[PDB]
Amino acid sequence: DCPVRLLNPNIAKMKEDILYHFNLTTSRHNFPALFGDVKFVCVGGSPSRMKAFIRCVGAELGLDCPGRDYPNICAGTDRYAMYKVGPVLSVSHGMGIPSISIMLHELIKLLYYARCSNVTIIRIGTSGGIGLEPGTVVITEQAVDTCFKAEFEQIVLGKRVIRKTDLNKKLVQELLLCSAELSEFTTVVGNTMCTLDFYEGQGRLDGALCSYTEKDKQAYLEAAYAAGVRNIEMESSVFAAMCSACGLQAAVVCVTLLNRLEGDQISSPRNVLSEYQQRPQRLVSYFIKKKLS
Amino acid sequence: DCPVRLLNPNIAKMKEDILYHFNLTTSRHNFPALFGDVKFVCVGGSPSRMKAFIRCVGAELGLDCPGRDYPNICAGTDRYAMYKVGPVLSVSHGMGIPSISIMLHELIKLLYYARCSNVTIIRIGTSGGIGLEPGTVVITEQAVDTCFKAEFEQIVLGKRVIRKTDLNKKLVQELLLCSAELSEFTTVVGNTMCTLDFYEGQGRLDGALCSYTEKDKQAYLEAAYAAGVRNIEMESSVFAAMCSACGLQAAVVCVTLLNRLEGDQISSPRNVLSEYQQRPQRLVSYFIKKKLS
Ligand SMILES: O=c1[nH]c(=O)n(COCCO)cc1Cc1ccccc1
Ligand SMILES: O=c1[nH]c(=O)n(COCCO)cc1Cc1ccccc1
Image (cartoon, rainbow over all chains, first blue to last red; front, side):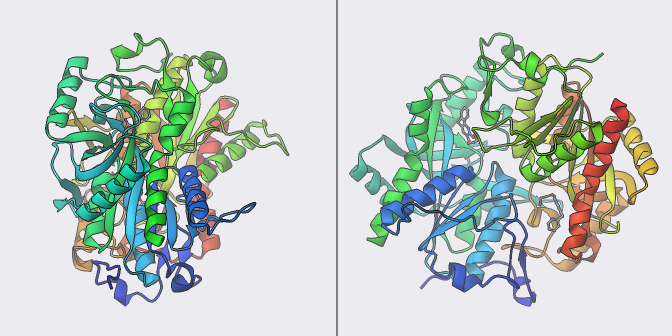
């Protein structure tokens, strides 16, 4: 029905291709054999979260592997980790726009080389909330920039280029339905601001550098809230800009680890934080199992 | 004798500080005892390279423990890895400005809490060459942007802020003298262009997306070269800006994996690429040995 597509005429003309940061090559690896059956891709910053994710899905799907292991498909490199259980692939992306951008360029080409179709991609992550209790799960409506607009900007051969951000509306509704059925945590739908710096780029007072006042950053966070922003993270704008352009249905599901209107460091005890950290995995693995049921 | 400094008044008012992405805190770790002897810090993208680096410099210094693991000081998290031997720290930083930015805010705080002084910090890494033979090591003179200027722009509370990039001129000279004495590979001094992204951000033709022609990327690379740029990477601009601000003497030493005027993928056999990858490590460990003897 809907094949993954690239927006690059040069790919067709290449004899072989190397997915440098995955250590996978079309000369050595049989892409349709390895990945042709992939229907769900889940991505997140931490390699150990992504392995925890695949194990969670394994057990949900009863495709479980009880007493046994999920090999890292990227063994041989440590730029990203990658795991697979049935039609589900789990991929780490590190932190920040450039780190996920590289992963996405290589992932989208793998999916294309695998002859994948009807792929859903969901980012699971963590975030700072604005005016939400800690632990709230946010399903992103729009991924927005530091002016609270639905855009991703980058420089390409010296020229400022802008792409619109786009997340599948129907997917947001499907995820919300799952969350209501689960009833295990508060879930809200709102806008997610994506920044390039975690400290000064998100109005923190605890960096090595801070050129502004508590009152300054508070006015900034309030202005974000008024424009519909509910959480803050570092990957969502390029993720939304790229995935739509390539024929993938995409969502972003992040848990808030603190309320930024009240401060900058996490004051949840360790057991409570571990619980928050598995909420996006819980929702998404539940959602996948539903789809495969 | 120059202590590490912070540009943030709020730090003195905090009772404790958690370096979230290192899994270290000031209440649970005696930073002066643990890190107080640090005089050199080497940073790079890959944790496995940074572990290889510490093993290398440990042997140079006569501190090597045949049959002992170097422990990861950041055990408990997988955001970054960190290793130590005597007065040398090795820290991974992942890929891109945001990822290294997080690491540098926390590292500079750590060095401050440890009461370190006269610290030298050197980034080792890989790069795309412009008009250099593959495997050439570039000691960066100025870290430049896509206009080819020695500036780093960031958004702070929705506002553009421009900072100067400053790499220590004396340290460049010392690394150049070291390279001439070692005489194990071609070493040049030149400018290094720092881009946000890797595929379209560096004019490659092999991404999932590509908006320009081979001719247009070639012209842009030629304009970079005419402006003094000899290599291209993804972290030098923010590294230079932050380190100079906080009183660390900083330098960047990268190896070129290809010449981008010839194309975008590595023609080098993998055994050769493996020798190239070890060259910045070789130079900097040698430099540290000289400095400490
Ligand atoms: O405020 C945040 N902002 C943010 O971009 N994230 C993004 O996930 C980034 C890696 O920690 C996560 C948080 C929550 C947080 C708060 C304090 C310490 C660590 C993480
Ligand atoms: O062209 C480059 N540009 C670039 O920013 N780097 C930076 O180190 C980046 C992580 O892959 C490394 C290179 C060398 C290279 C070339 C082809 C494939 C992989 C790496």
